[PDB]
Image (tube, rainbow, N blue to C red; front, side, top):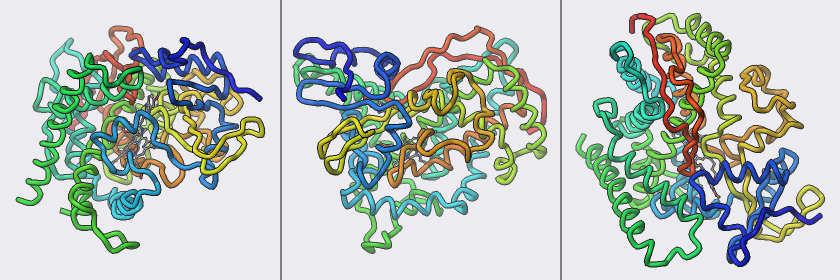
Length: 450
Ligand code: HEM
Ligand SMILES: COc1ccc2nc(SCc3ncc(C)c(OC)c3C)[nH]c2c1
């Protein structure tokens, strides 16, 4: 069969469809209109967007498709380098770093992060305990303070001290502009117009901000642990017997500082959004939190008991996966779905939020927030739920993100009652990644000591 395609703009083909602040949301609306697969063309480029589990389960066959660097990741590569997220699977530094950093995410490593997660989580609970009557909380701003600080502390023993700042941390401000710039570049017909010279200068300034922080983290450790940074600096790949070089290490630090907090901040923001909009769900989560979290701070085993809270998070990831796309390329000529022939090298994009609204898998209520969908995870078919990517190139931090988010959300629900005092209208800001923008709540302390 011939694949559908959205409206075209003469010689710019589909490119002007990305001239929006919300490209993923626009792509979802295209997919709603066109179905499980469509072609998207730009001058000199083609990609195919997949939205059904039927086709995406094929794309996830690593004997047929490998991770591709999308245009997005190519642009992020300018500051992520050949770090884990932006390396090709065949590049020597992908498997080497993977092997070197994997032990940083064992169950024993996670047990050793727990105390540091608690330290930051207590700082968030205390900020909110200390607000006066009728003050409110800027949700994604505070989630970002927590998640950036958690990855800085757990991974690098470095204190961002985000909660000691009224504005976002300068590292964040530069990160958000660089990510914005990467997204904005997706739409540029003429990337080397002189009209973009100033964006290029800002982009370079933002990269310098990020990098001087990296230098500071490296300086501090050399001056001063058994954490991510220890492994980056000293660990050896069991295959080659080599450690990472200096250049790749700096890319890993930037990589992990960003991937290791931005998407988790989004997830916690979306989860709280859905909880305040679904009071019976919030009540059931609050009741588990109270039942499980019996000590003044949570223990590692207790965080593992928060099953319903785990489900809430997975359901937030189902509706709004915070890294909403990943890309694949055909390793050889092959036919997708028995209907769409692909040549070696052809690129696919998995549109995760659409996968996650596939009614053949989830039933007709796909827009409802129902954590009970995850009551028995066995029943979900393969490759239906992919907020953490696929196969050997799946998220290395998945358990880190979920443990942190489960810990923090468990504590929030134990310690406060929440009010959507503005009747907030969901507004999703895109910076490649997804977050609610302007989401505010009020939290009334239950006065449970901490
Ligand atoms: C809820 C939060 C998170 C989400 C939704 C998320 C999502 C993803 C996705 C979709 C990919 C695959 C990208 C692709 O195929 O191009 C990925 C990879 C990756 N993630 Fe996460 N992630 C989260 C949290 C984290 C955390 C906390 C860390 C680090 C501590 C992390 C580190 C990475 C790294 C290093 C990779 C590349 C792995 C590799 O290819 O070797 N992520 N993640
Ligand atoms: C049209 O092309 C697009 C648009 C938006 C997109 N958002 C993304 S999300 C891409 C992504 N995935 C995973 C991680 C770990 C990561 O670092 C935080 C990033 C930036 N990719 C896109 C591709």
